[PDB]
Image (cartoon, rainbow, N blue to C red):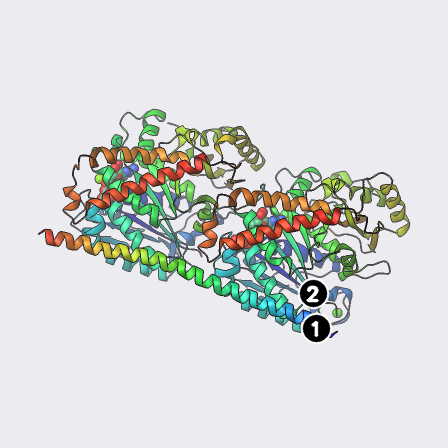
Amino acid sequence: MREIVHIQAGQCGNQIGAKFWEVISDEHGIDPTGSYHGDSDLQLERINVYYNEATGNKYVPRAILVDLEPGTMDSVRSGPFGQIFRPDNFVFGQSGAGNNWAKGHYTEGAELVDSVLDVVRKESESCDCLQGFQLTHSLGGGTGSGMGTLLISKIREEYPDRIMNTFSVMPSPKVSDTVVEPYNATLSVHQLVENTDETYCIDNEALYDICFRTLKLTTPTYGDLNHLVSATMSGVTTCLRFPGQLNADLRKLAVNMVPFPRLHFFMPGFAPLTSLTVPELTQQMFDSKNMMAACDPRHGRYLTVAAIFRGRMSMKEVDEQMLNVQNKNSSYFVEWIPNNVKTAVCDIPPRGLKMSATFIGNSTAIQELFKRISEQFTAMFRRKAFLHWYTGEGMDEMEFTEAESNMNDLVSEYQQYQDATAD
Amino acid sequence: IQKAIEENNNFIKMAKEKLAQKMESNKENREAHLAAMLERLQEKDKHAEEVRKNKELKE
Amino acid sequence: MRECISIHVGQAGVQIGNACWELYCLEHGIQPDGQMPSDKTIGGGDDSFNTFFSETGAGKHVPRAVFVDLEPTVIDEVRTGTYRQLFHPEQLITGKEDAANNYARGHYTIGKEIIDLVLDRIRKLADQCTGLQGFLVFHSFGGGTGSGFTSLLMERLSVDYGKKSKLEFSIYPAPQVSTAVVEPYNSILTTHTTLEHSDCAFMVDNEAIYDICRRNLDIERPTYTNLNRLISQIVSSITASLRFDGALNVDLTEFQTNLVPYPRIHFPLATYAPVISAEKAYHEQLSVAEITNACFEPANQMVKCDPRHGKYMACCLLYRGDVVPKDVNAAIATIKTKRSIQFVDWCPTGFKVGINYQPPTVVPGGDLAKVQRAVCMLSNTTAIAEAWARLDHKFDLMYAKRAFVHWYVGEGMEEGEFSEAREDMAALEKDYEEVGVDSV
Ligand SMILES: Nc1nc2c(ncn2[C@@H]2O[C@H](COP(=O)(O)OP(=O)(O)OP(=O)(O)O)[C@@H](O)[C@H]2O)c(=O)[nH]1
Ligand SMILES: Nc1nc2c(ncn2[C@@H]2O[C@H](COP(=O)(O)OP(=O)(O)O)[C@@H](O)[C@H]2O)c(=O)[nH]1
Ligand SMILES: [Ca+2]
Ligand SMILES: [Mg+2]
Ligand SMILES: [Mg+2]
């Protein structure tokens, strides 16, 4: 009876959001019609976290679908589980964002934001005790990046004591030739640093490399990248959806993962990744090749880590192997946060796997991600390239400089605590 | 026996006042924390108005 | 008279409370519906077990207990569990949002919204008592409710009941089963706020209980159920003098006189024996001497520390079962001639002994063997300060960087409360050093 309200904005946000509901609906035994046909009572014990139960014993995702164009949301409605979403929770426009953060944040998005809040408000009123919100979106586009960060600010104004979580997709030249993505992404990070409590960094650069290098996919599609996002999102929400002791709600997760409010950008990880023992799950789980953000954790230090093991296995062996990895890699865990690695175990494994492992790391090595975006940002901002797309919507030059400085400061803060010492 | 009564009453008294001060100081601090949060958010809305006006005048 | 009200706060306190009251019902012959065929006085009585159980006109024996948690899922198991008919609905109090492992939310933001209702329900129990003796408060150090709401409750109880005695059973955190990085913070904050409001506190180191279950009972990965059933036995031994009577029975308050030389030095170290599985206990009878010797094996302590490197200020032996003073005295004599039991120079060295003849009980499906005799030692040793030192060190590591402090400030707390609490702990560690120094 601790409800989460889900929001998905823009093309990317709606696609990964739709597949998120497909996966967890299968895990909870919910079919596309909303009826339960599972075999375990553990599936329904915390179903209220993500589902409303309309009379008739059908479960309706507590989900809101937003986009400044109908295209992506029309495929959701006509796809699998499209009929499970509440039709009133579809809020779309016709103008579009044109991959312009300013359009989605200040102009077109500002016209539609009020109607979205009406739906957020209606859903939140019927909550026994709202936990907070989780937003799926990309930072390289216009709607998900611009209007998504706008929704965050407006929701926070009305629910300032609730947790704001985001699944943010970072742009990569390997998965988009659209050139103004460094701008839209830097402007988005500027907002996320200030108005979110927890952000999972879904780096498209990492997803591509996993599909190509590891899984041997010459031409990775958005569907291939999204199969990783779905498995990851399922993993990092397992503690919220099933009975458990560790990080069972958004606030407790934030308290365990965020030692400083601005440093709330996590590095997801998943294992196995195959185109299986507990020692191998744990070794791979801490390997750079299994990270959903294109950063090497051995280039920084871990502030906090959450490990989630799924499937039937030996808890004694899990505890042993988690102690083993920390001891053998003690240099990569800050001394001044004792016992900063917490472990959860869920008896229910994902679909198609006998056992899996999900990794949530708050590592200073994440600066490599922001450094990559910053390098792409300054390369164009130095040339004032494409700024008329943004000044034409009313923006000022300072706002670009401010977003730049704030992201560069975020990098410095990660380096500060990476260099910090106990003695 | 009167001194025993006085000390026990002073312990109750001082415990009641210390707690009343903590709960009051805590309410004011938390309210000030939220006030600053919304005043920053409302400044963003005010800034969004300038952006939309800066564009309208550009036409 | 001499009624005792128990208060179980947070998940740890509630779940330990479930194990304790189940064990009590078995020790006294009370059924899950509260009926007790052996009790021939219906509706009331002055028997020893009435210190912990009230009686209704319908023959139900009701725990003098309140369960409080800021979220409902744990107490909900009590509402639907095997002993749901044992408690009146008003004894089980729940909120909708927990403290998110944040002392500030348990003591202020969330706790303040339910504190008045909790005090009201405690008052309802106190009004039923003709001679209330005090309270027993079960809570964890690490949880936001167990730390923050307990401190608030303790402060309020001092106001509403004066210096009426309040005893704690406190769960000291262990990495093997901990659920929050900030548990050192919450531990220091609640220890400081409760220090002046507690007369006696028994700390239970989860790592000590964890190791005991692994080593003595061969439980590979002990669960809370494993830990809590062991903790129940220790709590039972401690309260047995209040719930039973006998010629050789010694009241817990009389041990207290010896265990607390100064108000702040009120943290006894408990050691329990025998902890043995049914397989090893078979055809192996453990004598009085053997279980007494086990009390001085540090591996059987409830808190990890080395009394061999500290000084004793009191030693109490609480036996239960087939035990007579003759065998006790012989066992004690052997131990003094072969163990490093160094007392401070300002305390007598004699051991204080109590014997309850009711033998120990085990819950069905448990791991502990049923034995004919058991013992819990309660000693006041400077070595228990080791537990403070370990916790204070983890506090200093994080607080030097103000790690996670924003979660507390955001809920209304100030850094001054952190430093104030830490300084009180430093003085407490200092107090344990001074009491161990020889007199000039
Ligand atoms: N021995 C024992 N320890 C427990 C038990 N349950 C929780 N703990 C310990 O208590 C600490 C966490 O505090 P909890 O009691 O679970 O939290 P809480 O009091 O409900 O506070 P919030 O959940 O934050 O509102 C950790 O150190 C756990 O290891 C239990 O049943 N037995
Ligand atoms: N993983 C993934 N990334 C996407 C998807 N669609 C778009 N993106 C990324 O998002 C960015 C474009 O933003 P987009 O969501 O299409 O614009 P929007 O409709 O205004 O939100 C690009 O950098 C893409 O790599 C998708 O289905 N999956
Ligand atoms: Ca009776
Ligand atoms: Mg696109
Ligand atoms: Mg709890």
How packed is label 1: few (under 14 Cα within 10 Å), some, or many (20 or more)? few
How many discs appear?
2
* Residue most extreme to the left: B59
**Disc 1 and disc 2: Cα gap in Å?**
19 Å
- Tell me, for residue A274, which label it has, or none: none
Look at mark 2 in the image and give the residue it sits on. C134
* Residue most extreme to the front: C440
Provide residue A376's location: percent of width, then percent of height: 25, 33
Indicate the amino acid at tag 1: Ile
Q: Chain of mark 2?
A: C
Residue sitting nearer the eye, A124 or A188: A188
Indicate the amino acid at tag 2: Gly
Left or right position of C414 against A155: right
- Tell me, for residue B5, which label it has, or none: 1
Residue sitting nearer the eye, A356 or C133: C133
Vertical comparison of A281 with C282: above or below: above
Provide residue C314's location: percent of width, then percent of height: 79, 51
For the point 72% across and 71% down, which residue is it? B4
Residue C43 showing in the rendered view: no
How packed is label 2: few (under 14 Cα within 10 Å), some, or many (20 or more)? some
Residue sitting nearer the eye, A75 or C106: C106
Q: Are marks 1 and 2 in contact (CB under 8 Å)?
A: no
Vertical comparison of B32 with A101: above or below: below
Provide residue C141's location: percent of width, then percent of height: 59, 51
**Quarter of image, res A260:** top left
**Quarter of the render that holds ligand 3:** bottom right
For the point 56% across and 36% down, which residue is it? A319
Residue C44 showing in the rendered view: yes
Left or right position of A172 against C178: left
